[PDB]
Amino acid sequence: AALTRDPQFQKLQQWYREHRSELNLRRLFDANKDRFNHFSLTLNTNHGHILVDYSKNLVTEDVMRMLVDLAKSRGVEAARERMFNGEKINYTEGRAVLHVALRNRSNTPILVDGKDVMPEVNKVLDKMKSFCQRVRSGDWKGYTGKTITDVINIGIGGSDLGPLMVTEALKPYSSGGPRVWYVSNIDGTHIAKTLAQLNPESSLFIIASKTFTTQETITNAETAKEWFLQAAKDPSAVAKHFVALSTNTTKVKEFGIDPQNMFEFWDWVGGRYSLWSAIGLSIALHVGFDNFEQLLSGAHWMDQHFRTTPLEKNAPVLLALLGIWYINCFGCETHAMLPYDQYLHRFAAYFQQGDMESNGKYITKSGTRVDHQTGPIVWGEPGTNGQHAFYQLIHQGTKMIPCDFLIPVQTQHPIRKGLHHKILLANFLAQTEALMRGKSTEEARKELQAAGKSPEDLERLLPHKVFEGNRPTNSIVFTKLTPFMLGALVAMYEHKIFVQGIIWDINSFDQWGVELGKQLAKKIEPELDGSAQVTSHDASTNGLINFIKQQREAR
Amino acid sequence: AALTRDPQFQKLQQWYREHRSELNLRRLFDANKDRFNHFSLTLNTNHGHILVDYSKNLVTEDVMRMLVDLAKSRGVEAARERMFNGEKINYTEGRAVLHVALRNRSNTPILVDGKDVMPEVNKVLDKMKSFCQRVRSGDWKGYTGKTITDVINIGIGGSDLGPLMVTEALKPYSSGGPRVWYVSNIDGTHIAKTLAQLNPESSLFIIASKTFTTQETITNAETAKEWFLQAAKDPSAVAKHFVALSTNTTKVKEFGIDPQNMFEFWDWVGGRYSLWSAIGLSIALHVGFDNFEQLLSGAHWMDQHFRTTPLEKNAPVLLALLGIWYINCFGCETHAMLPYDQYLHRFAAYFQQGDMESNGKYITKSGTRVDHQTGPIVWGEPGTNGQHAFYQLIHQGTKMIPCDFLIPVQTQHPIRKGLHHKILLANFLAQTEALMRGKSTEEARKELQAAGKSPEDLERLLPHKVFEGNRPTNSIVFTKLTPFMLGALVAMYEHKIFVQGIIWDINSFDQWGVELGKQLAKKIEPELDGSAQVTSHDASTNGLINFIKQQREARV
């Protein structure tokens, strides 16, 4: 595969084989009091600063140089330019990759097949702005003349996770907006428990689906429309309560949706990169279009940082390279994302899709199977909650787990004269310090003697109180989690994912891996109907189906 | 370490070396039309059936036999009896491990230091029952004479995740109960945004902490009490709106809560095993104490299953053993929990604590460092949501990821004459079928030809459409997600975690790993006050602190 044959990758491997045991963070920090300055970036966006502190990583200046040389050798800069120039870098689907055009506040032309996309982008944005103002002002009324109080986004995957994560993160900015609800699961619990809390007269449903044929989304959409019409009766009332994020005008009209309330997007918007498009309509409804534009503008800022900054100082590149080091050299299967911010409680879950569906791949551009690792398993919960759930394992288990710790300097809720945020910050800082430093046998012994333990007591407990440390982390600290700042942070990780995928020589922008399960579910659905035993699959699938049929009729 | 020196483990590692490249699930199923019968268990709890189908695992009868031989050699049954008999098996802390006592509905005596714990378990349960009846009926009035409409649990870690997961999972059983809210993060967003939605006249706060010194919980509690008194003014009104769940009578009294408003538990209730105790009070308030007793009864049934069933047919043991196989022979770092149930959306997150804080260890009973893997990273989201997020990596990534797929046969919401649940069941079944079967080059080529692709386009696309398969799963199917059945399922994984801990010779029941971060946060706290530069740590900690101080004063 391309990566394994790359001479800079082999150089990196050889260094790792020879020098791994020099990489002790305590020793590295004791030997270089300038280490923070050498291995951190400060970004001034003009709308807050971002400090990317990567100094608690198992790197030296030589390792960083080797990693930048690998990004050069693997052609990261040229790939980036192909992305931004509208070239068809989604090569298995023959498609451009232009989430960057969605937020191109400069309106610099970006051509696909020699035709600037920016006018179509801005046309949809202008329709979003108009519709948002009509709904939020009370001008748009439901079928009995009431203003909209609840907006229900129905969609799966990329049509769900981004808008949910952002409206959760930007909840303080929703004054004057309707409540937002997200229905994604086909499990009928999800739509049913949502509908039970809503009034049809004042609810607006947003059906998010390019095809308007997606099975889970359209089934949920049909269930919502049945509930709605059980109240309203008149099919013409659907057009006051249902809009579409889609291009299938025919299916949209057939559903009962006025086609001027179809908000379009394009094939070069991947679902897991789509919150910047029409898919973000629920964001703009909730926090207002001005704040949605701020979200776009932050992403645009980070797009320019990624385009103009030398690789050795380029935040998404450096994040990507550190990840390559831990994945392909240390062999770490996972990457933890730990935001110390309750509003970001769905941030890690968003990047499960964005990272794992992008880079959970094993065929390269040439059709060759990889012979190395690709994307990691991403996971996490917000701090400080995760501290009382799983940090025991991060500190004292048998797994090396690279962690990104993120936090805003300024809280949206400075209650108690700042006391809560002060304690939050202190834990953010202490945890990465603890992971780095650990606590030696001698240090733990001293503590146990001071506590008065008997000599046999102390020797018993002592090994359990030792922290081996040397556990690496990134700390990402930013002034305040505003719409602009969130946009910049999300875009940063988008470009990290891109850089990693170029290095591995995979297509970060397709998802052929979802097809087999879809095909097999369609074959099973009709077999569940009626009471006959099923024999057409492997013995386990049959056995499960026949247990299901047996237990359908248990009291 | 003990495990590595165990002769049955060595025989497992040899079998793995000599036959690993022989375990292909398509071939196993083709060779053995009885593979599902031989590699599944059906349990009749008398309150729903449980099918634990472990046949899509990379195992043969010989592996399963070697795995059970390991369980006997590592002494799982004796260790189990020690736990159930009240011995001090939390050996680093000198404590018993008796969450099974909390749900011991048979009231068989369990002695600790020569005294039966059951009378006190039941005294607290009776107190919980009376309190829940009074609050739920409207008998219990707030300071202005109103009934309670909102219950707010303030607690973190083990005093939060359990009660939250269960109230979320059992939301259909909460008709007539007050709304429940969970405040856990120290981040002031969490309490602030909650208090803004509440009326002090009808909100009941529950302060949950064994110790009652958890800094996050006591700070949150003080913030809530300040807010409450801003409206109520009269400090004696606090006894009508605040109760405590703790082991520390004295710390609770020192906070200013009336002592008959304290619901006690005991040092042998680990926080991450504590929802069965007083810590479950918010569950009982929300769904009623009768449904809480069913939850306890479910766990009690699984406790008896675990205690009385031969190892080779014992559900928690078999799950544990399959985990050992994937962790210590295949080297899988992670274990995914994928319930096809939106009500279980917080189940995986609960077992992140239950599994990873228990078995995320590296020192054995003899004080020796392990020289093998211990507990995995647990993660997951409910299906079908996870399906559209990260299954691409499970199918076509470079990682082996043992997955548990869980689903109830009967939905709580049989809308559209069952259509939604039919589709959910189909996806539940197809995904494990797909992970097992894959799709070969030959099969993918035929599909592309049938779809009319040109030879150039076919050959360009073909390798991307191939699924290597052979990815193993458990399927856990149960009649219905009732209070009883949730109790049985949570207990089943508790005992899985116990068995794995005994096999690795670690302590599943301590958590010394959390101390260093707590000590270092206490030192940093005072340093954040005032504008002075901090120089007392490593350069990164200093540099972060000084950036925080710089930017605290920024106007964005």
Image (spheres, coloured by chain):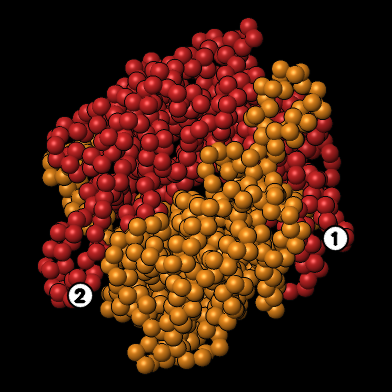
Chain colours: A orange, B red
Instruction: Measuring from the top left, give residue B272's x and y in whole percent.
Output: 57, 33
What residue type is disc 1 on? Gln
Label 2: chain letter: B
For numbered disc 2, what is the local secondary structure? helix
Label 1: chain letter: B
State the residue at coordinates (18%, 39%): B29
For numbered disc 1, what is the local secondary structure? loop
Q: Residues within 10 Å of mark 2 (few under 14, many from 20)?
A: few
Q: Which residue occupies the foreground of this view, A250 or B472?
A: B472
Distance CA(mark 2)–CA(mark 1): 63 Å
What residue type is disc 2 on? Asp
State the image quarter where residue B113 is shown: top right
Residue that badge 1 annotates: B533
Q: Quadrant of the C terminus of chain B?
A: bottom right
Residue that badge 2 annotates: B457
Instruction: Measuring from the top left, give residue B228's x and y in whole percent.
Output: 77, 46
Instruction: Measuring from the top left, give residue B136's x and y in whole percent.
Output: 59, 35
